[PDB]
Image (cartoon, rainbow, N blue to C red; front, side, top):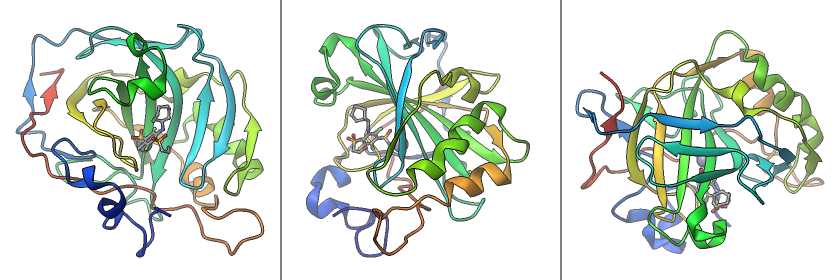
Length: 257
Ligand SMILES: NS(=O)(=O)c1c(F)c(F)c(S(=O)(=O)CCO)c(NC2CCCCCCC2)c1F
Ligand SMILES: [Zn+2]
């Protein structure tokens, strides 16, 4: 039932998911002059050399590129995190126009899209157990702006017309997610939640400062995707982002400056 339209969008989620109005909801605006540099943050460690992608899936909300997480191959560690988090999937949120689409904002600036690389805390044994825990997930968020093409994204863009509609999937092996990272790993971090229902408060957010650039043609192909299933009226998959939520009793920490 939930979605992104007038009738079922973010303003409505709280009726099914009361936690929508809870104390640690995501996304948030990152006020760069209030975030404080934290010298105790350990360097971040993104180890994706052994990452094994399997499949790409249009889930009716976004598209997910899924990884094999049945052993410790592609992990995120360090930074604010204790222990080892395993990459399970990534997806994006994007807009109908280049001036909107990201979930986090930076001094109220919206980017054209935001990539979320989702990882679960291996001390909880499976991701379904991890989402029930306040430190169960670590999501690495990366902003996209429109400018020069991102070569490492083109394999994703290419396969999208084979998963145009809700519930379609395609084989998607040997994709290397290192090709989606910016040069710097400087980041902001704060405790928050999944940004779609069920809005669980189980996420350590790590949001990179440096956006990646993608081309206008690349982002245009995201906007050709459909929210609907095959044989249903076409509703373009655009604007699948939740707006910034209240920061409440949280501090956003910077890894830099
Ligand atoms: N935008 S996000 O990174 O916070 C997000 C959600 F908001 C979210 F609700 C989900 S979901 O699976 O709970 C509902 C449909 O996507 C996922 N998916 C991943 C994280 C949640 C469970 C851990 C396994 C990987 C799926 C998810 F990645
Ligand atoms: Zn997301």
